[PDB]
RNA sequence: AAACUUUCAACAACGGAUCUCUUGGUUCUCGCAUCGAUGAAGAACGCAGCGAAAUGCGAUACGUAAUGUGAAUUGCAGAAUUCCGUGAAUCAUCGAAUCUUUGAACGCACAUUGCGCCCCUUGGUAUUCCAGGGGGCAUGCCUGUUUGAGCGUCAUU
C-alpha cells in the first residue's frame, strides 16, 4: 500500500490531448474585418 | 313702419348621407408536405446620387454571382456604349456566395457594447508586458481512442 499523509483524495492528473480534427471548421479564413479603408470612413469638413 | 322671431323657395355655407365604383374580406372545394446547433422563429442597429415610413438587403448592405428574356429605368439628376449584343432592366428565374449585434445561443458575464484563457502570425530593442489580424474554449448523452483510480479482484515474481 502507498503512504497517504493526507486524508483527502483528489482527482488524479491524466493526459489531455490537443484537438486533431479530420476536417476544417470553415475551410476558408475570413479576410481582415477592419483594414485601413474600413477604419477611416471619410473626413469631416465642417467650418469648425 | 323697421328691427327681431317663425315658415317656404333660390343661391351660397356647414357636414359627408345617398348612388355608382373595388388590386380587400369571408365561406366552400381541390392538390401538395418543406423550420432549427450546416444557428430557426423573433429582436436590435445599419445600408440608396437626392429616403422619414413601408418593402428589400447586411460593411460584398433597395444588393454580388449564375441562368433566362432581349432594350430599358423614370420624380429629377446622371450614366450613355449597354443596343446586329456574354447585353439595358426597381425584369424574371435562382442551384454559387455574402450574411453586422443578437436570439434555443454555446469561453464567463450583460441595467456593462464588461472580463478571461489557448493556437498561429505581425509590430513595439520580447516564451513572460502592450497592441493588430486570423482560428478556437457551453451542457446532457451515445460509440470509439487515450490517460488513469479502487486489497473489487486474478495470475505470476
Image (cartoon, coloured by chain):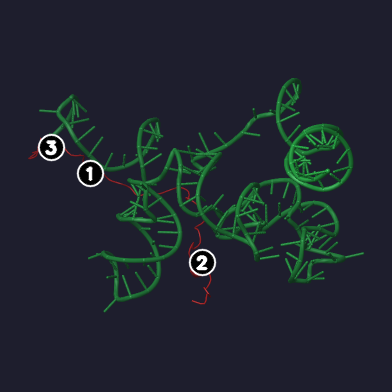
- As measured in the structure, the alpha-carbon distance from the residue carrying label 3 to the one carrying label 2 is 58 Å
Instruction: Give the foreground label among 1 and 3.
Output: 3
Side (left or right) of B143 relative to B48: left
Q: How busy is the neighbourhood of tag 1: few (under 14 within 10 Å), some, or many (20 plus)?
A: few
Where is residue A5 shown, x and y percent of the image? 7, 40
Residue A27 visible, this orientation: no
Instruction: Give the foreground label among 3 and 2.
Output: 2
Q: How busy is the neighbourhood of tag 3: few (under 14 within 10 Å), some, or many (20 plus)?
A: few
Q: Is residue B142 above or below residue B106?
A: above
- As measured in the structure, the alpha-carbon distance from the residue carrying label 1 to the one carrying label 2 is 48 Å
Where is residue B63 shown, x and y percent of the image? 66, 57
Residue, x 51% and y 61% (percent of image)? Answer: A31
Mark closer to the chain start, 3 or 2: 3
Quadrant into which the N terminus of chain A falls? top left
Mark 1 vs 3: CB contact within 8 A: no
The residue that disc 2 covers is A38
Mark closer to the chain start, 1 or 2: 1
Chain shown red: that is A
Side (left or right) of B138 relative to A3: right
Mark closer to the chain start, 1 or 3: 3
The residue that disc 1 covers is A13
Residue, x 15% and y 37% (percent of image)? Answer: A9
- As measured in the structure, the alpha-carbon distance from the residue carrying label 1 to the one carrying label 3 is 15 Å
> Under tag 1, what secondary structure?
loop
Chain shown green: that is B
Q: How busy is the neighbourhood of tag 2: few (under 14 within 10 Å), some, or many (20 plus)?
A: few
The answer as to whether the residues below labels 1 and 3 share one chain is: yes
Q: How many discs mark residues in the rendered view? A: 3
Q: Is residue B71 above or below residue B32?
A: below
Task: Tell me the subunit letter for badge 1.
Answer: A
Amino acid at each position: 500500500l502507498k503512504v497517504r499523509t493526507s486524508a483527502t483524495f483528489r482527482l488524479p492528473k491524466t493526459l489531455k490531448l490537443a484537438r486533431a480534427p479530420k476536417y476544417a471548421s470553415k475551410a476558408v479564413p475570413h479576410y481582415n474585418r477592419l483594414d485601413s479603408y474600413k477604419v477611416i470612413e471619410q473626413p469631416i469638413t465642417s467650418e469648425t
